[PDB]
Length: 166
Ligand SMILES: Cc1cc2nc3c(=O)[nH]c(=O)nc-3n(C[C@H](O)[C@H](O)[C@H](O)COP(=O)(O)O)c2cc1C
Ligand SMILES: [Ca+2]
Image (tube, rainbow, N blue to C red; front, side):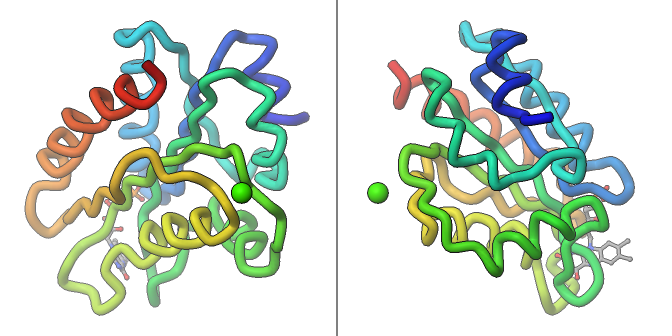
C-alpha cells in the first residue's frame, strides 16, 4: 500500500527509489540501501512505479527519514519507463514537502544533449516543493566510468548523512 507504512513496520528510515531501464540504477539503489546498516540505520530500495510518491508528505512521521533517488535519463531527456508516473506527478503537483530530506544521484552519459536531465529535474523540483537537500546532486557519466562516479559520490554521501542526523 504505502511505502511509509512499509518502512514503519520493517524498521527502515531510509528508502532508495530507482529509475532504471537496464538495471544500473537498481543495482546502485540496492548498494546504497545495504550501506545504511553500516551507519546504524536501515534502508530498503524500491521501484517508484509500485508506489504513490504523493506519500512523500507522510515521510516526516519516521524519525531520521531520508529519501534517495537514483535516476537514469533516457530518450530526449526522458525518464525511464518505471519513473514516468513519478515524473508526471512531479510536474503537476503543488504539495508542500516541508520536512522531507533528500539526495539524488543521476545516471547519464555526457554525449547526449540532455545529460542527466532526469536527475537534475528531480533534484530541482523536490527543493522547489519544499524538501531539504541533504547532499549535492551526483552526476554519473556512463561515457566515462559511472562506477567510479558513484563510488566517489557515495564515499562523501554517508559522512554527510551522519553529520546531518548526528
Ligand atoms: C538508448 C539510450 C539513450 C540514452 N539517453 C540518454 C540521454 O538522453 N541522456 C543521458 O544523460 N544519458 C542517456 N543515456 C545513458 C544512461 O542513462 C546510462 O546508460 C544509465 O547508466 C542507464 O541506467 P539504467 O541501467 O539504470 O537503465 C542513454 C542510454 C541508452 C542506452
Ligand atoms: Ca517549509
